[PDB]
Image (cartoon, grey):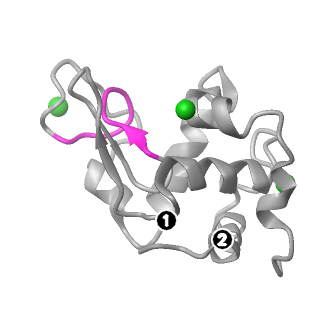
Amino acid sequence: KVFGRCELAAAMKRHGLDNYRGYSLGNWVCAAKFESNFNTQATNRNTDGSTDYGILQINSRWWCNDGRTPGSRNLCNIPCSALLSSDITASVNCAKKIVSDGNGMNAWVAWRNRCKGTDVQAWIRGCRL
Ligand SMILES: [Cl-]
Ligand SMILES: [Cl-]
Ligand SMILES: [Cl-]
């Protein structure tokens, strides 16, 4: 599913991501924009052989099981395929664990490079939330 911008903001809020660990909704929408362009089915293969999955490009090295990332963990206790669903529940619940892991949203390199320090409220501007 490719979400609309406000549609995704609303879904993220519904699932308790708004201001989670102090990160406003615009941060999460911005991260999703640059990780996946709001496409739940996004996948990307990393140099180390792990894969990133879903709207927030969650990585199989630590967070989910895909059966093809040697030496990896599955800390969200989910198949990586669950992160590709039109229903963002699994991605949100896993993101909550990731952002709580110590480095906040810096876990998403894209957020650090493209969202951090910017006017992230622009991402939810106009949205009925
Ligand atoms: Cl915001
Ligand atoms: Cl594996
Ligand atoms: Cl980047």
What amino acid type should be assigned to the residue bearing mark 1? Answer: Ile
Query: Looking at the rendering, which quadrant does residue 59 occupy?
Result: top left
Q: In the image, which residues are magenta?
A: 57-66
SS at mark 2 in the image: helix
CB-based contact (under 8 Å), mark 1 and mark 2? no
The C terminus, quarter of image? bottom right
Q: Quadrant of ligand 1?
A: bottom right
What amino acid type should be assigned to the residue bearing mark 2? Answer: Arg
Residue at which label 2 appears: 5
Q: Position of residue 22 (x, y in %)?
A: 83, 40
Q: Looking at the image, which residue is at 68% across and 29% down?
A: 104
Q: Earlier in the sequence, mark 1 or mark 2?
A: 2
The relative height of residue 19 versus residue 123 in the rendered view (above or below) is above
Residue furthest out toward the bottom: 128
In three-dimensional space, the C-alpha distance between marks 1 and 2, rounded to whole angstroms, equals 14 Å
The relative height of residue 32 versus residue 76 in the rendered view (above or below) is below
Q: Position of residue 11 (x, y in %)?
A: 63, 71
Q: Position of residue 37 (x, y in %)?
A: 51, 59
Check residue 43 for magenta coloring. Answer: no
Residue at which label 1 appears: 88
SS at mark 1 in the image: loop
